[PDB]
Image (cartoon, rainbow, N blue to C red):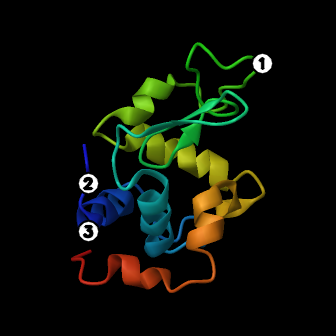
Amino acid sequence: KVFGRCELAAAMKRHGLDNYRGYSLGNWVCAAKFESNFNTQATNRNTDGSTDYGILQINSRWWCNDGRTPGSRNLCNIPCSALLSSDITASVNCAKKIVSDGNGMNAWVAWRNRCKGTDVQAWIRGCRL
């Protein structure tokens, strides 16, 4: 499913991401934009052979099982295909583990390179939250 920006803001909010570990909602939306373009079905292979899945491009190297990433972990205890559903619950609770991992939203390369240091609030401007 391709979310609209405010549509995703609202789902991310009801699931507890707004100010989760101190990251305001606009951070999560900016991350989602530049990782997946708000598309739940988004998949991208990494050079190391792992694949990123979902709204937040969660990787099979550490966080989910995709049957094909050697010597990988599944720290979220889920199939990676679950991260592609139009229901973002699995992607959101897995993101809570990742962001709690010590490196915060720096885990997300797009966040670090395109969101961090910017006016992220703009990404929820005009949304009814």
Q: Residue at x 41, y 61 (%)?
A: 33
Question: Which residue is found at the position 24% from the left and 77% from the top?
Answer: 127
Q: Amino acid at mark 1?
A: Gly
Q: Which picture quadrant has residue 59? A: top right
Left or right, residue 66 beside residue 38: right
Vertical placement of 11 versus 92: above or below?
Answer: below
Label ID, residue 3: 2
Q: Is residue 60 above or below residue 100?
A: above
Cα distance between the residues tagged 2 and 3: 8 Å
Q: Using a 10 Å C-alpha cutoff, classify the residue at mark 1 as few (fewer than 14 neighbours), some (14 to 19) or many (20 or more).
A: few
**Other residues around mark 2 within 10 Å, as few (<14) / some (14–19) / many (≥20):** some
Disc 3 target residue: 6
Q: Is residue 63 above or below residue 105?
A: above
- Which badge, 1 or 2, is on the more N-terminal residue? 2
Q: Residue furthest front?
A: 47
Asked if marks 1 and 3 touch (Cβ < 8 Å), the reply is no
Q: Identify residue for label 1.
A: 71
Q: Amino acid at mark 3?
A: Cys
- C-alpha span from label 1 to label 2: 33 Å
- Between 118 and 17, which is closer to the camera in this rendering? 118
Q: Amino acid at mark 2?
A: Phe
Where's residue 69, x and y in %? 67, 20
Q: Quadrant of residue 51?
A: top right
Whether residue 13 is visible, yes or no, is: yes
